Image (spheres, coloured by chain):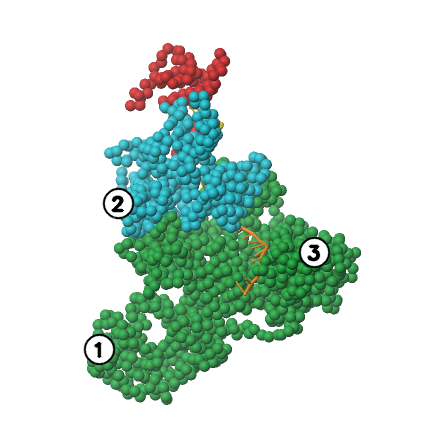
Chain colours: A cyan, B green, C red, D orange, E yellow
DNA sequence: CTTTTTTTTTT
DNA sequence: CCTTTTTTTTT
């Protein structure tokens, strides 16, 4: 169960009121719970703030137990940074100090946990228990959730779209929404919040991504072990399309724009992906493969040439890139049903969330596509709740999205260009529908909720 | 208000400060080099200068002199020549800059001021002091940074203003060490982002025209801009800042790529070997499997634009393109790699490699590498019961990866030549630094290899073939770990960490670039490579560019030091005492302290915290420490004792501290002393106000001060002196300077205890891999020198890989002769730090450990450059029990003879195997010819060759030597010279070249090709493995052909599929069936078994069907008739014999040609 | 191409979407001052003249409307009945 | 067998 | 031609 809001002051107030509700419950004129059950129920609640404030709440005794109990007091930098955090907390309020204290608290928390996660997911499993358990659980509230000691959480919408940490990795509640029960106060305001998270995605170069995909997919092959059964088939249509795409547009060459009115201002190509296509260039831009110069030249022709339009290339390149990411999602799900029981023991954590990080690793390593790890990881934070444009299925903007492409000269080099495509693969209304279609029972409590 | 040059137009450059005997040395060795080696060549002049008579003064007076000289040329007129002053410590760097600014002011020539005030402003404006980024930020005022943030429109970002608010918020609440530690980490991160955005907004499109207060604000925040702007000569930076580079307003400038003309003034040059090694051991480890697979995929068809801006660059990558395709086909790179064969997955595999004969691996079973085709996976596996080996793959993959990085550097250099001529918009940045940013970007983008962007940028700062100048100092160890990747369970990565060069190699690269490096240090020419540069490699690599000092110059310096330190004629005494273990002496003291306990051992465990483990050692350094304490207290005049131990006696082991404190107080009473002790004086202690407190006590109080420091805690810059008062100190002091330079009444230590220096093996703490490279560099740098024979160096490297305790590492270092010259470098510094003041006491005592009495007696250099206080420490050790020799240079020869043989045995075995694949590379055949061409044209070379250094073997006998070892077995078991006086002689008599050249046909042939007729009488004789296997094998090959040349027989080239399998292709007689050759030198070499021979026939019978063969053996017995042998090579009839074996062609008795045998051979090939 | 922040709002104003957005602020900016039970007998409400026309278009079900928002809508509804765009007809 | 401080500049 | 204040989390 989640109590998702959009402000920190509201979740802590809701948690505080919830704690008072358990204590102060005059059902039939008598307390509802005995003196002990209140402690059991209070233990089930968890508040997950940002990493910066999660650190500045634990005492120095808690962090000492973790640092000593994990052999981290030898890294020559963990102790160096923890000295500064310890030395900066001892000072007075001094709002000038606090703003700098919260910056370093978050960074140290990130560095500490990944070390705590590399050291724990390997071979020297520290077997967290005893007073060391209460120390990590205090530092990692999202660990009692993974251990079964709690199910109720209290976090902001941004924390629900970023995910929290346990001793293994970062847990994303979106990908594990089957059976959840969300409670959202002021549900209408989350449209702005979710949209703010969807606009934070990183721009991806289309030319590099398509050239990289074509080069590695031509020869690199997956293993023939049972753990990759019928996974090679998911990529077969993509391999043929990648070869056909490379032959059509001559991907062996690099791209560059030549002509007037093309260097003083870079072109921006917005696209609804269905029927709203707008170009920042005044006249249509063609794309010609020069075999003599071994260059692909984006140019403006002052004279419709369906074959060889810049917009047509970018639209096809976008479809292939989202095809790989879409196929990547199916392969990860396919991997988790070949290893769900057929793997037989070996590893617990049998869940598309637990297996997801490994299944991405094994497939991107065999294909030599480790540069796409971050892009694949982010796409799950957007379209993970999933696992069109066919005038034969439900066509709408709320699950199609929009794409903005910037075609400017690369950094440092004056004779190549890159298509920094920024995507919005869905809408907050679409994200909400995917959340419900995953199996979550959402409660929207707001006066203007409709 | 910047200052122009108009004041120097009236300068009298003819007027000069009066030179000094120390000043003349620097210029004397440099002027001759410029008029001999050219103007833009470079040099590595070291100067062995004593620390007290004028290192700075002369060093900075030279730096100032070069500053003044260039200004005249600039005034008479382009870019200014850089004048870096590189040191190790920030304290020393800032002190040097402050002294320089001091020197410009109060330097008076002939008693009158030299620089007018305006000139001082100009000269002070040329000097820069580029610190690290963190301290750079916390130097400028809030107003200076606010001008930059406002003037660059960076105040409109949430992150920039949020960070700068915290920096301003924290730096205002200063003056507390807890806050100080986080304002520095925060300052560095903000400085990177601020400059990164400043460089992003400046390198493209919009460009702010810097002027006025924006220039001052941007130059204060970016001192490196002052150099790029064009008004800055000198930089005052540490070695780390010199190796990492400094930002200007455009990018990160690296001085290593712009060394042509640099005048580096490196101070304490020997210490920079460990500093440079710390930068080299701090590089990123690269996955070899990912890099090779990525290179192979992005190269099969990824063209580069055909424009004049990229001409000749497509050709540099063609050989790499083919090799990548061949490499991928051989090892089946379409699959992913993964281990197999349990007993291999519990722990990872680490594969050390020298890229040379040393090839230690941590897998006790050799690991093969099969490429499974059903299960599409490359499998690394063990086979306990070959081309397909794991080590062969990794070495091959590493060579290709450094081939790409090497080719990448050539392409960047090629790109710069293509665009230097093109005068469009290249601006002033037309150097390899301005275009380095672009040339790497353009090429990595066309090939889609932008993943290698960092690996190319960070690595841009004589191959491993026997026909070259091979050495470890331009090569490096390669540590490779093959462990499972993170997350995925069925893939492995080759995390390779490289050391592609050495700090001595780096130093040579600076000089070959054009640097004029000056080494200013007392122990600048020590005979160790662990704590110094290898000056035997730097001698051979540099040659005459490594300048030296003549007899008169080093004699002049001693006279100068003898004048400014006139110990005896003015009257002083240097008492030297050697202290042993004095168990009886310490027992009485321990009993008297706490007699109520059962025994002295109870005192160790009660009031000293010592068990029965370290009791033998703690007593040794306590009995010897105390015995020196009381001898100092015995003398009332001396009042300054410095004990330089190895263990920090401080609040940590305070239990020991109070016992020795009591002993000093106890002896104080019975000797009528109010002594004081200054405990725990380590690097933290002098920092706050520390070492000035000790000076104040001797400034006013009456008593004896005893200081307990360590060698590390007295690094440099520390000035162990104090202000003297004549009321405090009477006739105890006495001046030693013949003349009188400024006074200021200062003295120094008069009695110092010198404990044995320990823990002399270098170390790094950056990471576990970071010191793994450091430890392997030390082992391979001792083996290259000759301190370790390859038998023990490989043993050390094998233990180092598996895992050793630091005690084991030092026990191996102690066993070499390098350790003796290392400890005699620590002492020579410690004794030299106490002589920094002329005004000295008369009863100067010296107490050192007796564990150094034998070590000190081994000192054998020339006192002509030594100090007055170190010769006294060594003269007592010479006039002592025994004086013997260690034979430094002859045990070095036994190791370098063994080493060069092992290199030949390992390299030749690889050259032959690489000639057993079809086809044979053009380089591989060409290298094979040169090995044989040089080996037998120059049987003995006069000097040490600089091109075939592994071909030869320096000998203690002229023209020959004797060896003993399995020539086809282990190369670690060889012994040479007097170890085996009954071994195999490698003289010219053994090969019997004289008998061969007596022949009337062989002799004329050698003269045309220059092949030797006799061996010279020099000591650079040939290697054993490459005298019988490569030389006598080739000597007969030339002799056989020359005899057969005069019988209408002509020989051609063996084709590229059976190369080295047969001598030459024989034609004539008109017969279609081709005629082959198998030339040998006698019957006692080259067994050529029938099964082995039959293998060669099949590989050539498939070639051209039927074939003929001849088994000519050149020299031997000409009397034995010829034999006729079949394809089975057993026996047969003549007319049914596929092969023929001639016992000899020239007699071994009187050198007579086998006329009958060739006539039958002539007749035979006519019948056949 | 780059439009002024003004023109972004001008284009949003011409739609009927903007009218149901401002009537969402008011409906919440008025229900937040209703969390107690002790109230004066003279609870006044003064609203801008630029909102009378907008508030006269509110026609949803009043079966959950707040007491203070209802009284805010009747006063603007007092001027008889005004024809609306019939949002469905212009949406089709 | 064997015997430790300390040092810089990045991120 | 409408007319801004405010927010969370990771980096
Ligand atoms: N003629 C001179 N020769 C050497 N040093 C001088 C002379 N005149 C003044 N000095 C001062 O004496 C000091 C000697 O240098 P110092 O640092 O004590 O020894 P070193 O430089 O050899 O380590 C210099 O710093 C310099 O300022």
Kindly tell me whether residue B706 is visible in this rendering: no
Please, what secondary structure does the residue beneath circle 1 have? loop
**Pointers 3 and 1 in contact (CB under 8 A)?**
no
Q: Are marks 3 and 1 on the same chain?
A: yes
Please, what secondary structure does the residue beneath circle 3 have? helix
- Residue on which the image places disc 2: A237
Position of residue B695 measured from the top left corner of the image (x, y, whole percent): 70, 54
- Residue on which the image places disc 3: B662
Q: Nearer the viewer, residue B1088 or A159?
A: A159
Kindly tell me whether residue A339 is visible in this rendering: yes
Residue occupying the point 48% across, 40% down = A134
Residue B1071, numbered circle: 1
Residue occupying the point 67% across, 54% down = B658
Position of residue B328 measured from the top left corner of the image (x, y, whole percent): 32, 57
Position of residue B1115 measured from the top left corner of the image (x, y, whole percent): 34, 83
Q: Chain of mark 1?
A: B
Residue occupying the point 29% across, 68% down = B1057
Q: Quadrant of residue A176?
A: top left
How far apart are the alpha carbons under marks 3 and 2? 87 Å
């Amino acid at each position: 169960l989640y109590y998702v809001t959009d402000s920190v002051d509201n979740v802590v107030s809701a948690k505080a009121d919830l704690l008072k509700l358990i204590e102060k419950q005059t059902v039939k004129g008598e307390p509802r719970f005995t003196l002990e059950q209140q402690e059991y129920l209070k233990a089930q609640i968890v508040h997950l703030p940002n990493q910066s404030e999660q650190l500045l709440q634990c005492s120095d005794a808690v962090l000492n137990d973790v640092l000593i109990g994990f052999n981290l007091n030898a890294e020559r930098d963990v102790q160096a940074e923890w000295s500064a955090i310890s030395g900066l907390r001892r000072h007075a309020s001094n709002p000038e100090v606090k703003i700098s204290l919260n910056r370093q608290a978050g960074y140290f928390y990130r560095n500490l946990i990944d070390r705590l996660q590399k050291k724990q997911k390997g071979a020297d499993r520290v077997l967290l228990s005893g007073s060391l358990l209460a120390s990590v659980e205090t530092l990692l509230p999202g660990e009692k959730i993974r251990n079964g000691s709690a199910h109720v959480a209290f976090l902001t919408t941004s924390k629900f779209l970023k995910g929290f940490h346990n001793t293994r990795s970062r847990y994303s509640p979106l990908r594990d929404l089957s059976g959840a029960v969300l409670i959202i106060d002021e549900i209408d305001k989350q449209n702005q919040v979710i949209l703010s998270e969807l606009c934070k995605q990183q721009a991806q170069d289309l030319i590099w991504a398509i050239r990289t995909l074509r080069a590695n997919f031509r020869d690199h092959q997956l293993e023939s072990s049972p753990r990759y059964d019928k996974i090679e088939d998911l990529f077969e249509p993509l391999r043929e399309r990648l070869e056909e795409f490379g032959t059509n547009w001559n991907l062996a060459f690099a791209f560059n724009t030549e002509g007037a009115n093309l260097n003083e201002r870079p072109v921006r190509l917005f696209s609804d992906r269905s029927f709203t296509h707008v170009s920042s260039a005044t006249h249509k831009l063609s794309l010609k493969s020069d075999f003599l110069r071994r260059k692909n030249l984006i140019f403006s022709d002052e004279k419709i040439e369906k074959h060889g339009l810049l917009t047509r290339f970018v639209n096809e390149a976008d479809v292939i890139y989202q095809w790989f990411l879409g196929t990547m999602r199916k392969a990860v799900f396919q991997y988790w049903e070949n290893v769900r029981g057929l793997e037989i023991e070996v590893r617990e954590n049998r869940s598309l969330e637990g297996t997801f990080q490994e299944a991405v690793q094994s497939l991107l390593t065999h294909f030599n596509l480790q540069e796409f790890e971050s892009a694949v990881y982010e796409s799950f934070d957007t379209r993970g709740l999933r696992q069109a444009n066919k005038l034969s299925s439900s066509k709408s903007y709320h699950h199609t999205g929009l794409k903005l492409v910037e075609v400017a000269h690369n950094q440092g080099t004056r004779d190549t260009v890159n298509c920094k495509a920024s995507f919005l693969n869905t809408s907050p209304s679409g994200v909400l529908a995917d959340m419900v279609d995953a199996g979550a029972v959402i409660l929207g409590i707001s006066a203007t909720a409709r | 208000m910047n200052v122009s040059i108009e004041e120097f137009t009236h300068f009298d450059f003819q007027l000069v400060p009066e030179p000094s005997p120390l000043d003349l040395v620097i210029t004397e060795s440099l002027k001759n080099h410029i008029e001999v080696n050219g103007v833009k060549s470079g040099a590595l002049l070291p100067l062995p200068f004593q620390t007290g008579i004028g290192k700075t003064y002369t060093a900075l007076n030279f730096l100032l002199q070069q500053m003044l000289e260039q200004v005249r040329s600039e005034l008479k007129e382009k870019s200014k020549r850089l004048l870096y002053y590189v040191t190790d410590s920030v304290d020393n760097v800032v002190s040097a800059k402050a002294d320089l600014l001091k020197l410009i002011e109060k330097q008076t020539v002939k008693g009158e001021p030299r620089f007018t005030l305006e000139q001082q402003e100009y000269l002070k404006a040329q000097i820069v002091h580029l610190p690290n980024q963190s301290e750079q930020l916390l130097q400028c005022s809030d107003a200076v940074l606010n001008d930059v943030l406002i003037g660059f429109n960076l105040n409109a970002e949430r992150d920039v203003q949020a960070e700068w608010s915290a920096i301003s918020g924290l730096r205002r609440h200063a003056s507390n060490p807890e806050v100080k530690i986080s304002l520095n980490r925060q300052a560095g991160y903000f400085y990177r982002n601020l400059i990164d955005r400043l460089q992003k907004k400046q390198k493209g499109a919009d460009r702010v025209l810097l002027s006025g207060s924006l220039l001052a604000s941007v130059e204060t925040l970016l001192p490196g801009e002052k150099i790029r702007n064009g008004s800055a000569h000198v930089a005052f930076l540490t070695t780390s800042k010199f190796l990492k580079g400094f930002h200007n307003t455009r990018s990160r400038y690296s001085p290593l790529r712009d060394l042509s003309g640099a005048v580096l003034i490196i101070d304490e040059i020997d210490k920079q070997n460990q500093v440079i090694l710390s930068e080299l051991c701090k590089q990123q480890a690269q996955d070899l499997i990912w890099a090779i697979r990525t290179l192979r995929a992005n190269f099969r068809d990824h063209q580069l634009e055909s424009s004049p801006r990229y001409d000749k660059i497509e050709d540099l990558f063609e050989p790499l393109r083919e090799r990548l395709e061949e490499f991928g086909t051989n090892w089946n790179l379409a699959f992913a790699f993964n281990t197999e064969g349990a007993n291999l997955n519990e722990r990872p595999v680490r594969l050390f490699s020298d890229r040379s004969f040393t090839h230690v691996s941590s897998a006790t079973h050799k690991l093969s590498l099969k490429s499974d085709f059903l299960r599409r996976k490359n499998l690394i596996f063990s086979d306990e019961k070959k081309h397909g080996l794991l080590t062969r793959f990794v070495n091959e993959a590493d060579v290709i990866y450094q081939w790409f990085l090497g080719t990448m550097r050539k392409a960047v250099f090629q790109y710069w030549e293509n665009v230097r001529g093109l005068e469009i918009e290249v601006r002033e940045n037309r150097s390899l630094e301005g275009t380095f940013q672009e040339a790497v970007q353009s090429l990595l983008t066309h090939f889609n290899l932008q993943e290698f962007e960092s690996a190319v940028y960070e690595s841009f700062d004589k191959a491993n073939k026997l026909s070259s100048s091979k050495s470890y100092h331009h090569t490096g160890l390669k540590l490779v770990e093959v462990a499972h990747n993170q997350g995925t369970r069925d893939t492995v990565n080759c995390k390779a960490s490289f050391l592609n060069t050495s700090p001595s190699g780096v130093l040579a690269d600076m000089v070959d670039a054009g640097a004029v490096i000056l080494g200013i240090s007392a122990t600048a020419r020590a005979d160790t490579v662990i704590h110094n540069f290898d000056f035997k490699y730097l001698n051979e690599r540099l040659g005459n560019k490594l300048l030296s000092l003549s007899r008169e110059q080093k004699q002049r310096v001693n006279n100068y030091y003898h004048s400014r330190r006139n110990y005896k004629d003015n009257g002083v005494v240097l008492t030297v005492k050697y202290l042993n273990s004095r168990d009886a002496f310490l027992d009485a003291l321990l009993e008297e302290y706490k007699p109520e306990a059962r025994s002295s051992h109870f005192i160790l465990n009660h009031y000293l915290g010592i068990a029965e483990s370290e009791q033998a050692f703690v007593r040794s350094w306590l009995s010897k420490l105390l015995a020196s304490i009381k001898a100092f207290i015995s003398s009332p005049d001396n009042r300054y004792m410095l004990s330089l131990l190895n263990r920090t006696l401080d609040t940590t082991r305070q239990n020991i501290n109070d016992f020795i404190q009591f002993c000093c107080d106890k002896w104080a009473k019975e000797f009528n002393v109010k002594t004081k002790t200054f405990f725990g004086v380590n690097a933290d202690w002098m920092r706050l106000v520390g070492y000035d407190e000790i000076s104040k006590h001797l400034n006013t109080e009456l008593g004896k001060v005893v200081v307990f420091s360590t060698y590390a805690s007295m690094g440099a810059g520390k000035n162990p002196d104090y202000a003297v008062n004549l009321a405090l100190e009477g006739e105890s002091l006495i001046s030693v300077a013949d003349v009188t330079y400024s006074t200021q009444l200062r003295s120094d230590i008069d009695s110092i205890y010198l404990e044995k220096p320990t823990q002399l093996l270098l170390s790094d703490d950056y990471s576990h891999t970071a010191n793994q490279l450091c430890q392997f560099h030390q082992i391979l740098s001792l083996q290259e020198n000759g301190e370790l024979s390859p038998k023990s160096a490989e043993n050390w490297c094998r233990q180092q890989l598996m895992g050793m305790s630091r005690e084991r590492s030092l026990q191996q270092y102690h066993q070499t002769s390098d350790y003796q010259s290392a400890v005699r470098k620590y002492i020579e510094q410690a004794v030299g730090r106490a002589g920094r003041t002329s005004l000295k006491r008369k009863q100067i005592l010296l107490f050192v450990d007796s564990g150094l009495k034998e070590i000190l007696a081994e000192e054998s250099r020339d006192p002509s450059l030594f100090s007055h206080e170190y010769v006294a420490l060594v003269n007592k050790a010479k006039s002592a029990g025994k004086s013997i020799v260690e034979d430094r240079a002859v045990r070095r020869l036994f190791n370098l003879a063994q080493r060069n043989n092992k290199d030949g045995m390992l390299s030749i075995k690889a050259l032959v195997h690489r000639l057993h694949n079809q086809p044979a590379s053009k380089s591989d055949i060409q290298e094979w010819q040169d090995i044989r061409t040089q080996l037998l044209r120059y049987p003995t070379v006069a000097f040490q060759p600089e091109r075939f250094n592994r071909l030869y073997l320096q000998s203690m006998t002229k023209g020959y030597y004797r060896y003993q070892g399995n020539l086809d077995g282990d190369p670690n078991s060889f012994e040479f010279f007097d170890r085996v006086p009954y071994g195999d002689m490698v003289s010219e008599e053994d090969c019997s070249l004289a008998t061969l050249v007596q022949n009337q046909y062989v002799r004329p042939w050698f003269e045309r090709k220059g092949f030797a007729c006799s061996w010279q009488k020099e000591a650079n004789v040939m290697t054993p493995i490459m005298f019988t296997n490569i030389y006598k094998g080739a000597l007969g090959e030339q002799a056989v052909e020359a005899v057969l040349t005069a019988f209408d027989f002509t020989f051609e080239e063996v084709p590229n599929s059976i190369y080295e399998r047969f001598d030459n292709r024989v034609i004539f007689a008109g017969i279609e069936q081709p005629i082959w050759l198998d030339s040998k030198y006698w019957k006692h070499e080259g067994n050529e078994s029938s099964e082995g021979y039959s293998s060669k026939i099949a590989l050539v019978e498939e070639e051209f069907g039927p074939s003929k063969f001849i088994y000519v053996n050149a020299l031997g017995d000409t009397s034995k008739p010829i034999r006729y042998l079949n394809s089975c090579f057993v026996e047969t009839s003549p007319q049914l014999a596929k092969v023929i074996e001639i016992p000899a062609l020239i007699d071994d008795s009187n050198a007579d040609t086998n006329r009958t045998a060739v006539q039958e051979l002539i007749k035979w090939l006519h019948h056949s």
